């Protein structure tokens, strides 16, 4: 605890390196950039007490800038570069060098982006004295394409291989460096590649039926053929030879359905290579990773240690530095096969960080400075050695010391759309809230403001969860995923991940690389809300938008001096929604600003709706509350309920031509029964004394409904067209039932003074224009009146009010008045059901005025007058008793009536409205309310 | 409107760009002639300096540049 | 994850301010707003809600009612 | 902290807590929403774990330097 | 409107710790700003962020900045 560094130079001096790095260029974007900067800055603060001791330069495209990419704000310096595909901005190695020398940097980090697969970059950088945080190019060459990889793996402790062209190998080079010279392995290349039609069959005879044939340049949907038969090999084989004419083709045995494991290798520039730990990455969709798990719990200790040893031997003999991954295919009987070496840090590398207590990108920085492994702090701790020292580590003798701590699950959040396949989507972000917790974290490449553009890849964020064992980690991940909120224009695959983690096959760890493909074909896109709730919620969103637009436009017209008639300010909306082929037709109205009523097929449900500041709605439906959001698309409504999504179709299917506006039909352009094509004008109408044509939407045979010369209404039926009916046939089957119903919050027998407020407020809202439709109005209003009349004649009402207002204020009331009031109300209660029973309003007022006649001064005055105001109001209401109060209430309602209807006498609607506008100059909401 | 507001400064630039193009080289192709003859037609007094200098170019690019006269004579 | 349902008391202030707990709750009941003695420190109101909505328990934590010994009674 | 420690209040414009390994935290308000008059102070809590004192300090310092809170208050 | 209500130069005055600073701000491009004080000029590359803030490049170092205008303070 005596290390005193402040600059990278001193650190390099003390820890025995040979290159000082003060500036790093990141040749990447999005997540990779974010993660690199964050991890290294944490380490920088740890060592230098300066979180910004290492400066990071980033290359910015205009697309990333406009999308407000997260890494931009984190960077120390930015340089603009040309936008578009990766070959202009990030996969251009010469451009990377040009920036690296233009801005004097000492290293370049590439990570898992687009340049770390190009072996030419390390050469260009090393020739100019720039340290690449990765392998030298000679390794990446020796780790070239697939034939060379399968061959070179067999020069030391031979991993099994599924006949990579064949099972033949070259001489032994256990720990010697060698290049892929085409003198000895050329034979293998001659066997690895095929020329004639019957060359590939020589592999098929040994590997068996599941043969995979690929061109040396195959990929992207072409150049790949999978042969399942024995006698159909020549067909698909010759096809592959034709897919990439003139190129060599190779034949290999196809993998079985088993597990995909990985070993993380880390190595310094002095020949020391170690295995960190493994990963199990067997949750894949079309060979794309989705979920990764850190402890490789499927492999037994013996076989897994063997796999680690093989990976390390490969890394040592080939001459790999900094960090990389070795993939293996693990068969259920305890037999592994080599797949490939990835010469770069992977995106899922935190999995092995969290269980090893290491920092890999910082380790890459320290390796690039030429620091051996036995001086890096975290490695030293991992092998049970004091961090603050310089003693060497015998990595072979102490290889049993490292041990994983816990179990980690890493779930990646993609931008695909599980609905209708997995098409990548894009657009703007409206909200990004990841609620972290103990043992759960995650990070994203985009913020709430910002978006995903065309060239912005999927995988816009990663969540990680730690636990002591598998089950705890699963539980943490599942809960965390159910709690996050991602909202935007794009689609966001999260719910599917939840469904997968709750599947028993996953939890029992009975999965393989073909698990998800099989599940996809079985149509497992579940996690939908109940239909009835979804219908109600969508109805409310549609109706609320329509109502708010009506209010806004009407009020805007009033501000400008225009008067619209009182049928454009409607309180009822008709909503139509198709779900799974079933059409639902509903009416939505309001009994108050917050009380909505949804009506279908003569049945009504009441919902309490509150507007949230974030654009969504807070519902209370059947006791349960819900938070909901809606997005209107061209032909769909996307309804989010909690964390579940339901999609409703907006009917546009019948292919009926309709007038977009009111007006008049003048003539038709084409013959009745003639064929029309989309975009061709079929009719001429006039509204506004200004002629507007009408283009057809679809190509088909048109028959006209209205005769030339006719009145047109918006959305009316003008002309039907016969099409070939591709789909969407008879998507009606109109639902004729009834919506849920069990409660209502009518307060049936609840306290009697709460019922007063309930019924009175409903009646007031009736007086303000909130009224049910025809068969429902006066079916409940009569009951409201009757219940109010019964409540107002009950002698127990005012004391209940007194109870509430007195109990809510125990403190700040002098004890004298408190005791007196309690006594008086108790007496009143004792006299209930007596003709001489009267509410002691005057006596309460007397004792309070007695204390005020004492009149304490100076903050003991005002406290008394203020904390007694509720009591004053109550006694003032009941000066004449329940009789006077009853009459007062009913009178006040009648006054409401007159307050409105005396203003609309004396002439026509518009004249009265103008009178109101000219009186209420400073507020148009008053006018609207009238 | 915005670019018109800074007309005087723009005129300074215009004159500098004329002098570096049609300075010690009294020749005018039939792409520069169109520009120069259009530029001399700006009658408003704010754009006088450019219309003047352009004129000086256009009229000066008819006299032989002293090598032809020396040689012939 | 929703085996135990949670009821919350919501003032108009917390609703207008889009308090985070509102969206998490399973059910909400409105209460009168203002100082704590109308909404959350009113033990009798807490009982009234607890019986109006049949709940089996009441958690108070470190708010305003957990310093009032009358509520457990 | 400027001019004493007077409690402030108002609307939130951004609330982004960047969690990390061994760091977490939570808040009673989201980016949309705010803090009203009766809404107490202490609108969020950050926690950091380490093997010892020094590591925990380091994690907390970095995480605090990385968060963004913007609003009227 | 006349072509002097669409100005490209702004005078800014700011007091910090009792000291008054008077500056002129103009532009050489939509993104290139020039700050002038007491006859000395500095160039800054400014980009507008979608979140309401500004991305600056000043002396090599980049910065992300935000402003809120109060009644009597910035």
Image (cartoon, grey):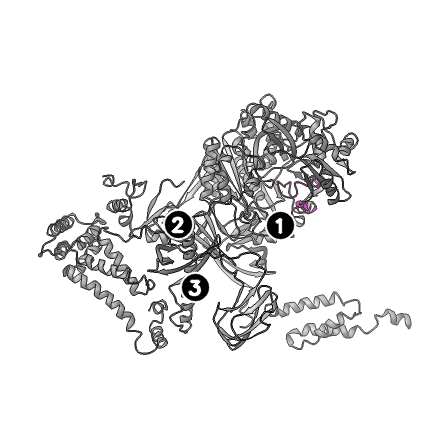
Among the two numbered marks 3 and 1 on one chain, the one whose residue lies closer to the N terminus: 1
Whole-percent x, y for residue A695 in the image? 58, 68
Residue A575 within the segment the image draws in magenta: no
Badge 2 and badge 3 both on one subunit: yes
Q: Which residue is mark 2?
A: A626
Q: Nearer the viewer, residue A121 or C11?
A: C11
Q: Nearer the viewer, residue A280 or A372?
A: A280
Q: Are marks 3 and 1 in contact (CB under 8 Å)?
A: no
Q: Which residue is mark 1?
A: A79
The residue at the far top in this view is A397
Q: CA distance from mark 2 to mark 1?
A: 47 Å
Whole-percent x, y for residue B17 in the image? 71, 66
Residue A111 within the segment the image draws in magenta: yes
For residue A313, above or below residue A742: above
Among the two numbered marks 2 and 1 on one chain, the one whose residue lies closer to the N terminus: 1
| Chain part drawn in magenta | A94-120
For residue E42, above or below residue A24: below
Q: Quick check: A155 left or right of B4?
A: right
Q: CA distance from mark 3 to mark 1?
A: 46 Å
Q: Nearer the viewer, residue A103 or A248?
A: A248
Q: Residue visible at 70% across and 24% down?
A: A174
Q: Which residue is mark 3?
A: A549
How dense is the environment of label 1, judged by Cα within 10 Å: few (below 14), some, or many (20 and up)? some
């Amino acid at each position: 605890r005596d290390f005193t560094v402040a600059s990278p130079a001193e650190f390099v001096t003390r820890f025995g390196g040979n290159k000082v790095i003060e500036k790093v260029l990141i040749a990447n974007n999005g997540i990779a950039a974010v993660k690199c900067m964050r991890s290294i800055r944490r380490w920088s603060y740890e060592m230098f007490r300066n979180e910004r001791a290492i400066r990071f330069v980033v290359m910015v495209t205009p697309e990333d800038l406009k999308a407000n990419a997260e890494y931009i704000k984190m960077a120390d310096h930015y340089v603009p570069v040309p936008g578009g595909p990766n070959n202009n901005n990030y996969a251009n190695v010469e451009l990377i060098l040009d920036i690296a020398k233009r801005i004097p940097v000492q290293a370049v980090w590439a990570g898992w982006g687009h340049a770390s697969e190009n072996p030419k970059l390390p050469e260009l950088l090393l020739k100019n004295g720039i340290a690449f945080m990765g392998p030298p190019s000679q390794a990446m060459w020796a780790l070239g394409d697939k034939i060379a990889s399968s061959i070179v793996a067999q020069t030391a402790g031979i991993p099994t291989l599924p006949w990579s062209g064949s099972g033949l190998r070259v001489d032994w080079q256990e720990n010697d460096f060698s290049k892929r010279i085409l003198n000895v392995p050329q034979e293998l290349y001659e066997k690895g590649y095929v020329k004639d039609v019957d060359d590939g069959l020589q592999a098929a005879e040994e590997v068996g039926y599941p043969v995979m044939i690929k061109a040396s340049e195959g990929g992207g949907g072409k150049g790949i053929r999978k042969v399942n038969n024995a006698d159909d090999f020549p067909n698909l084989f010759r096809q592959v030879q034709a897919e990439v004419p003139g190129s060599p083709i190779f034949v290999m045995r196809l993998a079985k359905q088993s597990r995909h494991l990985e070993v993380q290798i880390l190595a310094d520039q002095y020949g020391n290579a170690i295995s960190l730990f493994g990963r199990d990455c067997s949750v894949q969709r079309r060979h794309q990773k989705i979920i990764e798990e850190a402890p490789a719990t499927i492999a037994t200790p013996a076989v897994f240690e063997h796999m680690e040893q093989c990976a390390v031997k490969l890394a040592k003999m080939v001459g790999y530095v900094s960090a990389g991954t070795v993939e293996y295919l693990y068969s259920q009987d305890g037999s592994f096969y080599f797949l490939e070496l990835n010469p770069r840090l992977q995106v899922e590398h935190p999995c092995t960080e969290m269980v090893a207590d290491v920092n890999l990108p910082a380790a890459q920085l320290q390796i690039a400075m030429g620091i051996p492994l036995y001086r890096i702090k975290d490695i030293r701790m991992m092998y049970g050695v004091s961090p603050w020292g310089d003693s060497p580590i015998d990595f072979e003798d102490s290889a049993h010391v490292p041990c994983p701590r816990g179990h980690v699950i890493a779930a990646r959040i993609t931008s695909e759309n599980p609905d209708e396949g997995f098409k990548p989507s894009s657009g703007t972000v409206q909200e990004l809230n990841f609620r972290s917790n103990k043992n759960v974290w995650g990070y994203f490449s985009v913020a709430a403001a910002g978006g995903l553009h065309e060239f912005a890849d999927s995988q816009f964020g990663h969540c990680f969860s730690w636990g002591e064992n598998r089950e705890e980690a699963i539980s943490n991940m599942v809960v965390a995923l159910k709690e996050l909120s991602i909202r935007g224009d794009f689609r966001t695959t999260v719910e599917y991940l939840i469904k997968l983690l709750e599947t028993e096959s996953f939890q029992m760890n009975r999965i393989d690389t073909g698990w998800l493909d099989r599940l996809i074909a079985e149509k497992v896109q579940a996690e939908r809300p109940d239909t009835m709730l979804g219908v109600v919620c969508g109805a409310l969103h549609v109706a609320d938008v329509s109502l708010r637009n009506s209010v806004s436009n009407f009020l805007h017209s009033l501000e400008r001096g225009q008067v619209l008639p009182a049928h454009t300010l409607l309180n009822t909306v008709d909503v139509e929604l198709i779900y799974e082929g079933v059409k639902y037709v509903l009416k939505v109205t309001r009994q108050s600003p917050n009380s909505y009523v949804v009506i279908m097929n003569g049945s009504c449900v009441e919902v309490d709706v509150h507007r949230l500041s974030d654009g969504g709605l807070l519902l209370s439906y059947d006791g349960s509350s819900y938070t909901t959001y809606m997005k209107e698309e061209v032909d769909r409504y996307r309804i989010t309920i909690g964390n579940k999504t339901c999609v409703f179709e907006k009917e546009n299917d019948p292919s009926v031509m309709r007038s977009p506006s009111a007006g008049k039909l003048i003539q038709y352009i084409v013959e009745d029964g003639g064929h029309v094509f989309a975009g061709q004008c079929y009719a001429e109408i006039e509204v506004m004394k200004m002629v507007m044509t009408l283009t057809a939407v679809e190509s088909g045979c048109i028959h006209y409904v209205k005769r030339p010369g006719a009145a047109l209404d918006p959305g009316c039926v003008l002309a039907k067209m016969q099409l070939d009916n591709p789909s969407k046939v008879q998507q009606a089957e109109l639902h004729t039932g009834s919506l849920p119903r069990i409660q209502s919050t009518a307060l049936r027998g609840e306290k009697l003074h709460r019922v007063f407020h309930y019924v009175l407020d409903n009646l007031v809202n009736v007086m303000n224009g909130y009224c049910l439709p025809d068969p429902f109005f006066s079916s409940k209003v009569k009951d409201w009146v009757e219940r109010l009349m019964k409540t107002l004649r009950d002698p127990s009402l005012p004391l209940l009010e007194l109870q509430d207002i007195m109990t809510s204020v125990s403190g700040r009331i002098p004890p004298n008045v408190e005791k007196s009031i309690k006594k008086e109300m108790a007496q009143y209660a004792s006299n209930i059901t007596s003709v001489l029973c009267q509410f002691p309003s005057q006596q309460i007022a007397n004792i309070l005025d007695s204390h005020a006649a004492t009149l304490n001064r100076k903050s003991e005055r005002e406290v008394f007058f203020m904390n007694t105001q509720s009591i004053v109001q109550l006694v003032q209401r009941y000066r004449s008793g329940i009789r006077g109060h009853m009459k007062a209430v009913v009178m006040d309602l009648l006054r409401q009536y007159l307050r409105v209807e005396t203003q609309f006498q004396n002439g026509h609607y518009d004249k009265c409205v103008f009178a109101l506008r000219e009186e209420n100059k400073s507020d148009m909401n008053t006018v609207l309310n009238y | 409107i915005f670019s018109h507001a800074q007309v005087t400064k723009k005129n300074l630039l215009v004159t500098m760009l004329i002098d570096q193009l049609c300075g010690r080289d009294p020749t005018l192709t039939d792409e520069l002639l169109n520009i120069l003859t259009e530029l001399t037609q700006l009658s408003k007094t704010t754009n006088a300096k450019v219309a003047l200098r352009a004129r000086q170019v256009l009229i000066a690019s008819h006299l032989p540049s002293y090598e032809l006269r020396h040689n012939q004579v």
